[PDB]
């Protein structure tokens, strides 16, 4: 088409041809009306779950919060004895975080057991 | 007067031994007016054409009776021998835009007036005059209308994988017993499934808590996917649907014959590719197209909105798609020399203004588990018998071992 | 009402007879698995398997209730999903309702108005005499006055042209005003164009209008 | 304009993470 | 007294003679309906974007219908002014 | 917000009688051919609810587990004076 225009065989040409330095110098052109250019075409719950793309994208504040809340619960459970810390408190907490624990069981333990409400609220959220 | 066959508007039935039809009352209790109508037994070509008189009735004949009562008309009901609405078609003699079908019969002088669901068209209006429409309706499409995979929609091996997880904990509990039996696997199976089943206890508690949280997370992932997501599979949006705009042999759709829809498509030169595939799926009448759609021969059938919605109400297996396009209304077509145009228009307008059209609509137009859980119920019911049988077998085996 | 089809379980056919039979089957299998007490233990175990958190109730015979527990929890999850899918979201049903005949027979006095010197009043004059007489009490000076009266609660309904009411409902601020569903128009007619009788312009005006309708030039303007 | 579910691999990764955490916790019991 | 309330809350709040037990089992079963409804309501109110989903475009009803509650304008007599002045609708 | 409308391009304002218009157009086309505009865009233009409720609930529960406990302890002391 460009060669046809060059040798006076075509006064006007419209064939969706591109505009570059070489074509512009050889033959004149008017104001473009459609955006175009050089591009590359390739083939087009799938993303990551249980991680930053799913929830807790920053993945630091919540990560430390879920541990410090358990630490505070263990500390207050120890302080409420007047039971014990470390293994017993950790086992009790990890048993009360969910409502399907069988081997989990005056008023201090019952008062700490209200953390099951927080656990179920967190599960619902 | 000649009319065309249309189930929502013109019911045609064979006559009894006396040449008439049974006298019946509608659901509301009003009498069902029927008339003796002359026409061919089979309008399709290549058939033993017999002009036996059938019995025809419906909304159109009721409107005709009302018009005759208001204008002292002695109507003579006739049926279109061609069996089509008719338009300008080229059959022979080169350039010949001669009207055929009902329009051709009216122009030939055989018919004096037409009462039928005849869509108002500009080309028809050029040579015929249409009175005030008695109803307004457009064009839509008719098409036959998720959680069957109760276990897993895909990757069914997961049920095994989580089961393998039980193993990777069961053998664990034995090891702690050796460096401190047989119920570890049973408890692992029945910890989430409630059925009543020094540091070793702590490790057991933590490991089973992790297993339980993994299981509940998997169950939430599986079930929360089965949600409000659309159950229908890509319902036709309407005339602007890209699938309709891109004809293909995989998804075929066409009209019935050279009706007003065909004329509208002919005028719309944009859908040139649509016409090519449409011409290959024509049908003799609307009933054949409806049967084909019910038989899944046609993916979708484009036709008048009123007929399609009436058929959807009558046949719930087929549903209507598309909002509205080519909005028009049915009207009475008469020759330009007929002096009843003003009388017919006034009578129709008066009847529609006084609520007669509402009564006509009520009498004729206005009418009236699975693998989600039944599959798993059947599976568990079948498995219970095998389970109790094997329980009896193992009890007998234990008794034999104890006796020996 | 409650525990019916409107409440939940939009099918409501299979489960309402399935629950009793599955409970009976569970009782039978648990009383057969003694090598126990029917009322004292079978029903308790059935309730403990229907829902996870329950009362602490207890060979492979008692082990094999895991399949029933799994079926029950799957059924509960499916019920929750169905409730979630069903919880995501109109009484006149036309002019044939009894309210238009006896507006004053209800506890709240129904107040419907129209615009006189129009088509609606002319139609209702020759079709409903007493209804028109009651309507004359609530005459409106214009479309805007009736619209603001209906919006503010002064009027309970407004009968007028279908196209104008549809336009107002479609573009209403807040979408607090709606028409009588769809297709409930009493006297479905059209506007058209008025011409003098015997004029030679109708013969081509009608053809031009029908050509415009057929060519699709009307849809974009609408 | 006119012219022109269920779990995934990361769930298994989280399962691996929790299994590793459980093994790390149980190492203390094993050595004891 | 007081211990009975804690005992009942241990079942209601999932914290872990037959005449009372038969109705207690029904109460425990119904207690799960409350939490299921709470979870369903939270999911329904969380999956839906409560505020407006931004401006769709030129044909947005907010832009096509002027209102002091949602003001919108250009800066000055720039190219946007000429582009709008070209259109008449 | 908004996908796109009134798509156009930024132009170099020049007078009609200015003889540099063709040279400017050729230079711009040559520069954009090799990606100079892309490099300039990269160097100048191409630059870089749940938490709140979670924190509120965590604070509420950690406050309650102590406040309700001390209230119950005071009640026990009153009942066992
Ligand atoms: C038809 O209309 C004319 C004028 O409107 C009237 O004089 C005539 O009586 C009408 N025909 C019948 C049969 O009523
Ligand atoms: C109806 O009109 C016809 C005129 O064709 C007349 O002979 C007949 O008497 C009319 N019937 C009545 C009931 O007026
Ligand atoms: C309606 O017509 C009456 C005369 O019957 C007149 O008094 C009244 O002002 C008219 N109202 C309007 C809004 O034109
Ligand atoms: C434009 O570029 C050409 C390149 O050869 C040059 O000869 C010409 O002088 C330039 N135009 C002006 C006004 O300098």
Image (spheres, coloured by chain):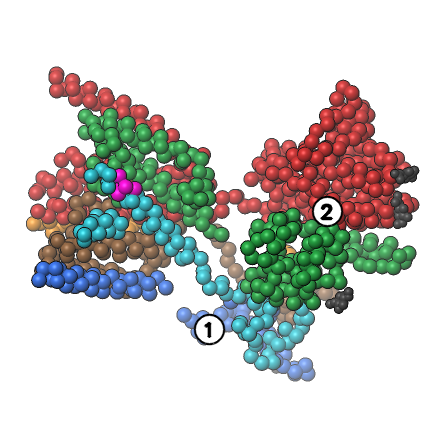
Chain colours: A brown, B red, C green, D orange, E cyan, F blue
- Residue C34 visible somewhere in the drawing: yes
Quarter the N terminus of chain B occupies: top right
Magenta region: E22-26
Q: Looking at this view, is A117 or B157 the one in front?
A: A117
Q: Where is residue B301 in the image (x, y as percent from the top left)?
A: 65, 40
Quarter the C terminus of chain B occupies: top left
Per the rendering, the mark at residue F45 is 1
Task: Say left or right for B283 vs C54.
Answer: right
User: What chain letter is assigned to the residue under label 2?
Assistant: B
Give the residue at x 72% y 53%. Answer: C129
Give the residue at x 16% y 18%. Answer: B400
Q: Is residue E23 magenta?
A: yes
**Residue B354 to residue B11: above or below:** below
Task: Say left or right for F9 vs B89.
Answer: left
* Label 1 crowd (10 A; few <14 / some 14-19 / many >=20): few
Secondary structure beneath label 1: helix
Instruction: From the image, tell me which residue sits under label 2.
Output: B355
Q: Position of residue B395 (x, y in %)?
A: 20, 22
Instruction: Name the image quarter holding residue B76.
Output: top right
Q: Position of residue F67 (x, y in %)?
A: 20, 64
**Residue B98 to residue C213: above or below:** above
| Total labels drawn | 2
Q: Which residue lies furthest to the top in this view?
A: B404
């Amino acid at each position: 088409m460009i060669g046809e225009v060059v040798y006076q065989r075509a006064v006007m040409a419209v064939g969706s041809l591109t505009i570059n330095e070489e074509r512009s110098e050889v033959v004149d052109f008017s104001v473009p009306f459609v955006e175009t250019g050089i591009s590359v075409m390739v083939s087009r719950v799938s993303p990551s779950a249980f991680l930053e793309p799913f929830s807790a994208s920053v993945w630091v504040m919540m990560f430390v919060m879920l541990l410090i809340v358990s630490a505070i619960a263990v500390f207050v459970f120890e302080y409420f004895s007047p039971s014990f810390t470390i293994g017993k408190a950790i086992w009790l907490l990890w048993g009360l975080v969910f409502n399907n624990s069988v081997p989990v069981q005056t008023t201090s333990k019952i008062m700490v057991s209200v953390w099951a409400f927080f656990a179920v609220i967190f599960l619902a959220s | 007067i000649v009319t065309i066959h249309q189930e929502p508007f013109v019911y045609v039935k064979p006559t009894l031994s006396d040449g008439t039809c049974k006298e019946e009352f509608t659901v509301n209790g009003d009498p069902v007016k029927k008339v003796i109508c002359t026409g061919p037994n089979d309008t399709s070509p290549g058939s033993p054409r017999h002009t036996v008189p059938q019995c025809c009735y419906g909304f159109c004949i009721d409107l005709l009776i009302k018009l005759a009562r208001t204008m002292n008309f002695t109507y003579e009901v006739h049926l279109v021998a061609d069996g089509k609405f008719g338009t300008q078609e080229r059959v022979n003699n080169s350039n010949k835009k001669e009207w055929n079908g009902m329009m051709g019969e009216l122009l030939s002088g055989q018919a004096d007036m037409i009462v039928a669901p005849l869509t108002i068209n500009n080309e028809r209006a050029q040579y015929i005059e249409f009175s005030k429409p008695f109803k307004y309706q457009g064009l839509t499409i008719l098409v036959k209308k998720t959680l069957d995979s109760f276990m897993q929609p895909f990757q069914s091996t997961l049920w095994l994988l989580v089961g393998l997880s039980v193993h990777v904990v069961a053998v664990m509990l034995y090891l702690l017993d050796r460096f401190s039996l047989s119920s570890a696997m049973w408890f692992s199976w029945g910890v989430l499934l409630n059925s009543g089943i020094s540091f070793s206890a702590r490790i057991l508690g933590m490991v089973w808590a992790g297993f339980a949280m993994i299981i509940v997370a998997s169950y939430t992932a599986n079930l929360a996917a089965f949600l409000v997501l659309d159950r229908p599979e890509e319902r036709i949006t309407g005339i602007n649907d890209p699938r309709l705009r891109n004809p293909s042999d995989k998804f075929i759709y066409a009209t019935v014959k050279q009706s007003s829809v065909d004329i509208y498509f002919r005028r719309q030169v944009e859908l040139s590719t649509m016409y090519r595939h449409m011409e290959k799926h024509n049908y003799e009448s609307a009933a054949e197209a409806i049967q084909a759609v019910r038989d899944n021969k046609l993916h979708a059938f484009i036709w008048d909105s009123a007929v399609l919605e009436f058929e959807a109400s009558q046949k719930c297996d087929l549903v209507t798609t598309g909002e509205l396009f080519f909005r028009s209304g049915f009207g009475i077509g008469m020759r330009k020399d007929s002096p009843w145009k003003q009388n017919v228009s006034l009578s129709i307008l008066k009847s529609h203004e006084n609520g007669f059209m509402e009564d006509l609509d009520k009498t004729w137009v206005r009418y009236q588990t699975f693998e989600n859980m039944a599959g798993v119920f059947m599976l568990v019911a079948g498995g219970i018998v095998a389970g109790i049988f094997l329980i009896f077998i193992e009890i007998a085996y234990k008794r034999h071992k104890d006796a020996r | 009402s409650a525990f019916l089809e409107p409440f939940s379980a939009s099918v409501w056919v299979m489960m309402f007879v399935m629950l009793l039979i599955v409970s009976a089957i569970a009782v039978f299998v648990f009383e057969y698995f003694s090598p126990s007490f029917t009322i004292g233990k079978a029903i308790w175990l059935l309730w403990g398997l229907v829902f996870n958190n329950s009362v602490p109730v207890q060979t492979t015979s008692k082990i094999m209730v895991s399949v029933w527990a799994f079926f029950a929890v799957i059924f509960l999850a499916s019920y929750t999903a169905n409730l979630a899918a069903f919880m995501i979201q109109d009484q006149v049903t036309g002019l044939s309702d009894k309210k238009f005949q006896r507006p004053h027979d209800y506890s709240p006095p129904f107040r419907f108005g129209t615009v006189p010197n129009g088509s609606t009043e002319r139609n209702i004059r020759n079709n409903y005499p007493y209804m028109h007489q009651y309507m004359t009490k609530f005459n409106q000076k214009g479309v805007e006055d009736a619209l603001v009266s209906l919006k503010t609660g002064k009027l309970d309904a407004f009968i007028y042209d279908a196209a104008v009411l549809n336009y107002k409902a479609g573009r209403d601020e807040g979408c607090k005003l709606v028409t009588i569903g769809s297709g409930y128009i009493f006297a479905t007619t059209g506007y058209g164009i008025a011409l003098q009788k015997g004029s030679p312009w109708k013969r081509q005006i009608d053809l031009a209008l029908l050509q415009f309708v057929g060519d699709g030039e009307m849809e974009e303007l609408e | 304009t006119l012219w022109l579910s269920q779990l995934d691999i990361d769930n298994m990764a989280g399962v691996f993470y929790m299994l590793a955490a459980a093994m790390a916790l149980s190492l203390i019991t094993f050595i004891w």
